[PDB]
Amino acid sequence: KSLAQSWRMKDRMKTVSVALVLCLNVGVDPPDVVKTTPCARLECWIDPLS
Amino acid sequence: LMEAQEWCRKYMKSGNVKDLTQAWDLYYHVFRRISKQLPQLTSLELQYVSPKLLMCRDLELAVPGTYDPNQPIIRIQSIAPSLQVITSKQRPRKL
Amino acid sequence: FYPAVSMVALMRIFRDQSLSHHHTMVVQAITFIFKSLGLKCVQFLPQVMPTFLNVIRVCDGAIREFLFQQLGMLVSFVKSHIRPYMDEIVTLMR
Image (cartoon, rainbow over all chains, first blue to last red):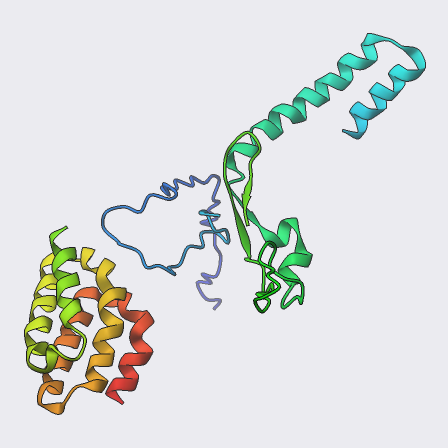
């Protein structure tokens, strides 16, 4: 008596497209966070300020 | 630039303006591109431009326009890692 | 302007000879200044902090338990920005 074998992924989703909304007004620190002198300034492996 | 050089050199054997229009195409091309680049070269990371100076530590050679015969030598301990660029007609560096 | 003037007058006292009596007074003011400013206090840090920590090592134990109370107060307003001076603080505590 073979079991109700539920191992399939018949729900085969596919990610089609991508939005990269990216608010990053460079050199303009927003009024919330007053940042440090040597702060973390990297941003996808780039110094934006350089 | 290699290709624009080719066409301007094909002018020197034939002497047609039809060679030259193809060259000025590519010349104006890079001219406009480079004109759109230079406004944002505000600082020069010294590794990219001149590695020997980044590598340079502790030269006996004195700091330029410091040498006095009556003082001891203030010598180039090390060059700064990146250069601020003033925007003018001649874009001077602040080394 | 105002915080900057006061900070300069206070720190002009905050150097041994006059403080023999008026340590406590100065530090009470500072702590109130930073409390009042928010995070805009951060700009005065490099003026205050080097003198401040040297005061602790120099002064008598009559005061010293108070200074630490107020140091801890500076720490709280400033938060992460104190990180540069942390070595000296830990040396003092130790």
